[PDB]
Image 1: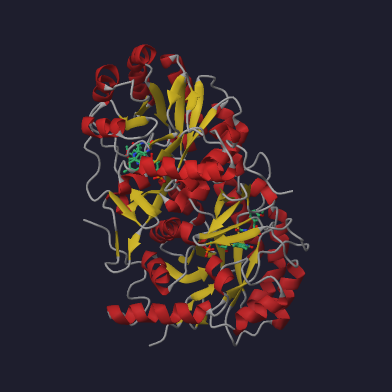
Image 2: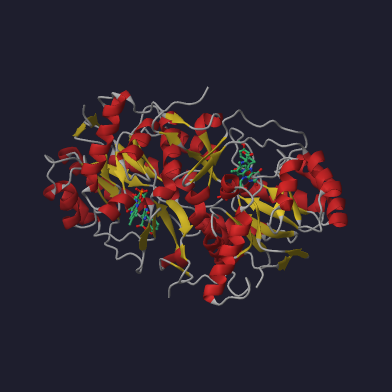
Length: 313
Length: 313
Ligand SMILES: Cc1cc2nc3c(=O)[nH]c(=O)nc-3n(C[C@H](O)[C@H](O)[C@H](O)COP(=O)(O)O)c2cc1C
Ligand SMILES: Cc1cc2nc3c(=O)[nH]c(=O)nc-3n(C[C@H](O)[C@H](O)[C@H](O)COP(=O)(O)O)c2cc1C
Ligand SMILES: COc1cccc(CCc2c(C(=O)O)[nH]c(=O)[nH]c2=O)c1
Ligand SMILES: COc1cccc(CCc2c(C(=O)O)[nH]c(=O)[nH]c2=O)c1
């Protein structure tokens, strides 16, 4: 019985990795993730310049999940490129680098410079589309014309297989349109579903206050709140993009939650909130729990059940 | 101390009512809700003709909430209008009738008939902008030009104060655009935030199956999953629509959860999943729990704290 996968011309001990943004901002964070039992890691979404991000408090967690408005704090592209080019030990596990430029030209400039490191060292790009463009317009993946522009420009500039991190959708028309846009781009080889469920509001009853400072308390939701939303998006894109991989992200706290993602169609399974709360020891637990479910069911590999969710009659 | 309030030229014993679709489809159901301690009730969203809805199973509930693809099963508009005109006892509490025609023309036709019953009896209209998926077209509330048409046509056909049931939004630009649409219509006097979080997917690990039959398992989410989403929408529209009431719906299982909705801006608080799960006794509990929290805080009225959620610096 084994959790091994081979995808995107890389080998993964297991499907688990951090979600972008969690335990991956600094060198220390990345070394931690690399030392962990995860199958892979992804770096913090970066911009060309370093950013301090929003004022604190900007992340809070509770029994059913988390809310954040971090504001994209990161050490800048050059740092993450250096990590990929010179610091990461590729013999431990594969690395993904997430980018989240604030404009199409910022993304273009970064992927141009990432390309030769991707070709030589095998770092994999995750382009964050669940991200701001012009303020007063919707996030890029909620603006299908902007999304198409970003993918056309990045595809031309980068020229290598990459993946995309998508926000959740809630309307079948959006699943259809979004997948049709992605399917225009043969270099988009993986689709990570989902980013945080946007602009939730957590309020603390005793203090009568929101719990994060930015944006009058509005921020993206993760964790137990979002698992059925995550599963729906994984399955919706799994069905609509048969020549791409789907990576699942959202609501994973247990090997059972991971097994659901994989039944829905997930290849890799990313862990955000639960990892932020539990720490990297979660990866040994999740591996053990998923293997126990597989043993009970007589499954020896992930492919035996990936995308095999049953429908009713 | 009592929770009675006056809105829309009606008196309410308390701010609680059922969510449209729950405990409100048949004459039995409407009599049950009338006999409950709720402050008001709303009927099942109706179409001009009766509908059987989708194949079963089409609703399921879990510790953290529910998923449904009911398919607008309903007894038809003539039935609900007859209930409003002849059967309902207005001395007990106010009645809202929810309409969800499958086209603008259907909604126009129904509202032209409701108008004199609204004048004579005081039934209130809640216009549901959500409908079964039509391939190629987004939900009405997610297509701002369609939304503007519906509201223009209904406002003209009806001529009296009404409200609108909204799905959730997840992007600040969308809040801005949606509220600006709504603010074009002075007869829209209340906005109910929110309908179920669309197209989630619940999977059972043991059976490896989805749990509802229609739509390959995809359905709207209610319950604990959606409380922060619901609060964010309530507050976003409370802030943007100062000349309107906001009715909160989503994730209410306790007087604390109701308290948070009211803090966010809610005038009435609607209860769906929890009501479906617990039954109509829930209203006496929610009333007791909300009065208990008020008493611990020193609040004597709902107006003292409605909309008064605090932000940080
Ligand atoms: C503190 C924090 C920072 C995040 N930063 C990023 C980011 O930089 N890029 C990104 O693609 N997603 C980011 N996200 C989203 C996560 O990658 C993940 O999509 C989301 O939290 C849902 O997964 P979960 O339910 O396991 O938390 C962040 C989430 C959290 C909680
Ligand atoms: C079984 C069921 C049927 C519903 N039918 C309707 C409907 O006819 N009209 C409507 O506006 N919303 C309908 N809804 C949505 C609810 O009114 C409510 O917006 C949603 O369930 C969120 O509230 P909750 O978290 O309390 O369940 C339905 C919900 C459920 C669970
Ligand atoms: C630039 O300000 C931003 C506002 C919202 C989202 C983002 C992208 C980064 C990001 C963040 C973040 O850094 O806030 N949090 C998430 O949950 N997902 C994300 O993708 C940037
Ligand atoms: C599958 O049937 C529908 C899909 C979307 C919307 C509607 C309208 C009635 C409705 C329903 C329903 O009857 O399925 N369920 C909801 O959670 N909200 C609603 O507004 C039906």
